[PDB]
Image (cartoon, grey):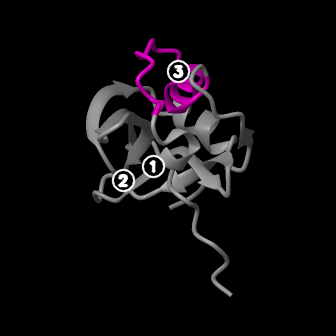
Amino acid sequence: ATPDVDPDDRVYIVRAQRPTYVHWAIRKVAPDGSAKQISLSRSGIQALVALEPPEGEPYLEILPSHWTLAELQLGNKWEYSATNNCTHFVSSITGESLPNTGFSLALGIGALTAIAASAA
């Protein structure tokens, strides 16, 4: 509903195994069942923090206030690399140690989804 977190909202780390790498993200589920999810997408070859459709399986539940941190980084540009990827985005937010499985050796930046363009 609002930008800020509702008291009954629950936030999770989620894990989406793709062929060549693992997609890490943070999801907020509401009482009615609706969900939002934030991770790294790309525009061209430039990675950035962006909303995305819910995807992957709940990995660990975390305190809701973690969502706000991820929400505040929406739009931030990201230096995508082997040592700086989906894993590192979620680790910096949550402060939980994730295994570095969030980079594709074959696809690289091409692993990330292309962000949706202007509605106009």
The answer to whether 48 appears left or right of 101 in the picture is: right
Q: Quadrant of residue 82?
A: top right
Residue 33 location (% of width, % of height):
28, 57
Q: Is residue 104 magenta?
A: yes
Q: Is residue 89 left or right of residue 13?
A: right
Q: Is residue 99 above or below residue 22?
A: above
User: Magenta residues, as a range?
Assistant: 84-105
Decide: marks 2, 1 in contact (CB < 8 A)? yes
Q: Which residue is mark 1?
A: 37
Q: Residues within 10 Å of mark 2 (few under 14, many from 20)?
A: some
Task: Report which residue position mark 3 lands on.
Answer: 91
Which residue was labeled with disc 2?
Answer: 54
Earlier residue among tags 3 and 1: 1
- The x and y percentages for residue 56 are 29, 43
Residue shown at the point (59%, 19%) measured from the top left: 83
Q: Secondary structure at mark 2?
A: loop
Q: SS at mark 3?
A: helix
